[PDB]
Amino acid sequence: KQVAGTMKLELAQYREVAAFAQFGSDLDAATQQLLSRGVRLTELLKQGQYAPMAIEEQVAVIYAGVRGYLDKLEPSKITKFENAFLSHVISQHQALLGKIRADGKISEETDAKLKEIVTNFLAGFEA
Amino acid sequence: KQVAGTMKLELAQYREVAAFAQFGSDLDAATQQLLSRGVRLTELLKQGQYAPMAIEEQVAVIYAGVRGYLDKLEPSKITKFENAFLSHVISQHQALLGKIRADGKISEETDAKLKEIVTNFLAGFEA
Amino acid sequence: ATLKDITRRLKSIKNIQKITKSMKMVAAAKYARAERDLKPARVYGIGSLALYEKADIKVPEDKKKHLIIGVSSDRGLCGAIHSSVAKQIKSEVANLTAAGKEVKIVGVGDKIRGILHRTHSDQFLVTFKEVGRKPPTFGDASVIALELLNSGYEFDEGSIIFNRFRSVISYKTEEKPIFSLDTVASAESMSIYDDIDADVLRNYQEYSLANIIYYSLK
Amino acid sequence: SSDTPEGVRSGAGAVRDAGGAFGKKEQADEERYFRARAREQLAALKKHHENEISH
Amino acid sequence: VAYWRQAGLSYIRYSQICAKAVRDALKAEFKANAEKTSGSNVKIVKVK
Amino acid sequence: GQMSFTFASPTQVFFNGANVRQVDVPTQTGAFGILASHVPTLQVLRPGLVVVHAEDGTTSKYFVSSGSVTVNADSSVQLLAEEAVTLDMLDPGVAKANLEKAQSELLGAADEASRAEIQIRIEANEALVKAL
Amino acid sequence: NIVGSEHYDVARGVQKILQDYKSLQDIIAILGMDELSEEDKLTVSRARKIQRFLSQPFQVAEVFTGHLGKLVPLKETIKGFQQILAGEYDHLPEQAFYMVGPIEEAVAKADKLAEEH
Amino acid sequence: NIVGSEHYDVARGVQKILQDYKSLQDIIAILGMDELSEEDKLTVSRARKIQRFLSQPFQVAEVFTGHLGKLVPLKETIKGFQQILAGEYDHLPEQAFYMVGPIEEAVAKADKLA
Amino acid sequence: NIVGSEHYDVARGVQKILQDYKSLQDIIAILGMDELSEEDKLTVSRARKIQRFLSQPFQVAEVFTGHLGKLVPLKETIKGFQQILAGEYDHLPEQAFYMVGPIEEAVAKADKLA
């Protein structure tokens, strides 16, 4: 509820402005922040088959994109980013996900603790 | 029958060119005239509820419009002009609306007598 | 489909059909006006050009700067008008860069700037919008030509691209040069001429810049 | 059809009720134009001088 | 060279003023043809 | 003889390929006369009247504002002007009042180029009255 | 004769500008928004503020929204809509009227959006 | 899993460029071709060759048109839809892609209409 | 093979000339009049003679409109339109053809004008 409430409201503003297929005005600073964020949030919602993720793993994927840590990547590589980032959390950071599950909520100690690992990953993932 | 035979032809020429009103300023002066009479004849046709008129008062209001005595008055004032003009001719020209009710037709004597009436009222009107 | 689906799609192509009939008679009465007003502006446009044909003038070997003036409208719905002049401006810039010349371009329409906003966003000088709603006049050919001088960019050759039409059906995108520099207009074919100095030719060569824009705008 | 009272005739507001290509091209053009007017009317609304003295 | 020269002006800036005075000396009948030309409609957009 | 005189406003055309033997033009750097074979020049205009002498008995008293006279190698001229009106469209009465008001702002001009703009305005109204 | 002549010419003034907004959407689909004239770029922007001002945050829908429950009286509903029609709020964007109560909160919500630029 | 990760990715790119072409047919029919974008004059210009590359001359229909019946392998109908979705063949007309076998006969047909 | 070749090629040309006036009436209404050729100005003039020569006063209306009711046999109607097409009676004005009987009464009405 603390991470999807500001994901739903960023998709609702994407569907209203991205129905053209014929753009004539370049609003590069005005709406291209809004119209090129919802492309990343949509491809974050794709999934495979017979692979149900856990609830605390789901927060660590949505939070990586709603606060804007994916806005530099190419759109063809966001699905490649996630199946590499899914491995880096489930192996080395198990006690972090044990706190999100057992408490049931994310707190301010956990919020900045979750902020660093996505920045160390993005500084190391790109080649 | 005498006045409404031209009104029926005038309104029918307006409904042909009603689709040019939304973006029209680069048209011929006849077409700008055909729009100008069609809007002002429409405002004569509107009528409040539970106010039925007389045929002698009906023919006078149509005679004021189909002749050309309204193409300089603003299209929003055609309702206020009509309620002012009708209360005038009931009290101050009652002896003309007894020579169209009893005669049935409109002669050449009443054609001139009605002609200076709508020219006297239109001259000093806006006050 | 269902009966409710057929009726709703059928009514929607009635309104699109009625509106494009109304927008045919509107833009045809704007055409007959622009045909009458061209013939006084043709000979006045021909006469201001007519000095350069009775002289062998050409930009001889190499000059350091350049201007391309792209002439179009601020409106759409006109087919391949804007796409042709955007095709001709990209052909000339890619050819002159083989000679090492620095090129600065200027668009007098919105839809020239909107197309070229990606590839050439750093080679713009100024852009002039609100063009084509009202008919063009000579004062707007003086507003543009004044600001082409007092900008800080001192250039030495140039050219203008526009759509000179042949008939109702067929137009043509064309090319005309602008000898703006006084010294390239100081050649063998001007020594025959009279007492014109570099101050009189400075005032005269500026005025023919406002007469090629008004020719292009009509 | 339409040249009689019987046949189908189209009313006003029938491109948006269809919901097709032109019905979606109209909604995203009223929004991408009135998004810039929420910029110019909000940037000039910060030019109240009494607020700047409070700043 | 004149006073509009050597002070930093252009010949269009000369030609704007002396043609504007002719449109002020016209009568009431031919004032609409001075309103007709009146070519101040082009906007200015420089990116900086 | 064997000349061509062209006189065109932006919006209207007076003469097209019809020459009459003598054209009087007010040049920026003086004045000149065209007499069927003048040595060609490229001159620009000052505010002043153009009196084209028609063959046709009489003359033609036009009044240009700022244009360009191009007499060329073959005997043919091209006089193009911006505001080329006749005499009867102008009023003398408004032209008298416009002079001294622009002289009043001449002392009240603090800058050096803004005062130079005022010197342009008084010159055009000076040729306005004396042509009338 | 029942709701008074002041409420009556406000109700029909709202429906007339909404119905005339419907016929204008058929032009924008082919022409566009910017190619319209300046006179009917204003009757659209007055209509869009009337669409959004009608939406009110309900009380029993707090668990859907989180917003608070408003209850505008009758004398304030008419005076809110006279001023959008007459043009006394042409200096605000459309978002300042979405999910508000009376017209007083439409300008308080207008400034709070401005400062976060 | 069953058909692979390379067969599955080219087969889903074909159904993506043919669905976006299907959503523009309501506009191309009214406002023509000159009202699209510049990147959307490439979805149209590529889907109109994949449509013609899904044509094939059959073997039992030799007595209809008199053309030879062609058979392709499965490994070569993956290579034909990669060199179109990438943009390797953006210098050929659409009618050169019409009624052929594998991708090598498409370039052996465009040299005829030279 | 039913009404013969004399009825056929007369009544065929009437409906063809009445189409050319239907197609040229739109350029004149939108663009203007004088741009079209001199060979087309006669087709505009002749088709306003033909579509008024189709009028005919009836015997049932003798009391009201005052004219005389005309009953035209078959061999006059074919002979009439065979001459209007060839430009044989083109110099006469338009109102000589309005509301007449045969072609004989047409030239007897051009004399009464002025």
Image: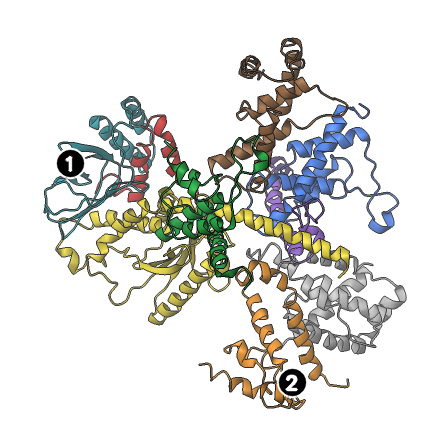
Chain colours: B brown, C yellow, D purple, E red, F cyan, G blue, H orange, I green
The spot of residue C62 in percent (x, y) is 28, 67
Locate residue F41 relative to residue H90 in the image: left or right. left
* Amino acid type indicated by mark 2: Ile
Label 1: state its secondary structure.
Answer: loop
What is the distance, in whole Å, between disc 2 and disc 1 at their CAs? 85 Å
Q: Which mark is residue F91?
A: none
Residue E6, compared with residue I2, is above or below; it is above
The spot of residue E21 in percent (x, y) is 31, 32
Residue C63, compared with residue G107, is above or below; it is below
Locate residue F92 relative to residue G29 in the image: left or right. left
Q: Which mark is residue H78?
A: 2
The spot of residue I2 in percent (x, y) is 56, 62
Name the residue nearer the viewer: H2 or H64. H64
Label 2: state its secondary structure.
Answer: helix
Name the residue nearer the viewer: H26 or I98. I98
Corner quadrant of residue I48: top left
Q: Is residue B30 visible?
A: yes
Question: Same chain for the residues at labels 2 and 1, yes or no?
Answer: no
Locate residue C198 relative to residue B99 in the image: left or right. left
Residue in view at x 54 percent, y 37 percent = I69
Disc 1 chain ID = F
Disc 2 packing (10 Å; few <14; some 14–19; many ≥20): some
Q: Which mark is residue F54?
A: 1
Q: Is residue G80 visible?
A: no
Residue in view at x 46 percent, y 62 percent = C120
Name the residue nearer the viewer: C70 or C184. C70
- Quarter of the N terminus of chain C within the rendering: bottom right
Q: Marks 2 and 1: which is nearer the front?
A: 1
